[PDB]
Image (cartoon, each protein chain N blue to C red):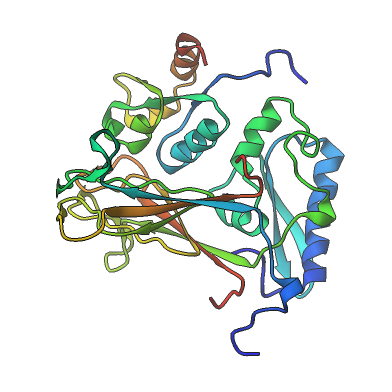
Length: 163
Length: 82
Length: 81
């Protein structure tokens, strides 16, 4: 989910600044994610993933920023502000909240072993506040055992977390 | 108080959005609506895309009795050009 | 800024939902795209979403095909990415 709606905005800002501090220090280029563990109002660095992540989608929804277009424009030598058009830090939007689930063929009644076989029917929902980023799921597709079990990533977004 | 909308001046204005209605109107046949069976229907998604589907799914027979709408597509982004 | 940072064509060294996500971004940025696919992944949606696509890792297991550094580079150079 995004943002971390169960933590106070101040504490979240602190975590974001620490991530920025690390990245400024090493002159980080392109997209990356800094990962922390958090416990009773302290936070501890665990990892940097120096790449886009599967859950980038929900950050895009709550900021209005297209992260993957940004990666490509960054690699073309463009300036985040002048050319890519992102605002200064304090102007970066924070628009409601967003949730992502990955729908997979893992069978929860069979120890989450991924099912294989032919997809007979695949009807995907839409509407307001729904984003879909599909993997391999279409009517007639044979799910093989060779790859991951993802069918489709679903994200929802709205002004309020509960919606 | 209950629905939770802000006061007028606080009503957000977030980028821009465009809607097209995809229909069976054949632009090469004077926009007469086509009918018949839908063999294949694969709908896009991703960031900045919203779909509000009418009657379009693989196997659906489009009749001549109703409007020709298949799916409403909206896109949205910070900038109109995007 | 490295020399050669201008782009007309991009290749995704991946498969599945992330490859489709990148192709979408490329197309919106006016770039043409290139997919790679293992033989066993030949029905993957990402293969058909690109402007052109190429089989890689011939005769390897499917995961090793996607880890085949030199065959991926071969495709990038051959396609003019």
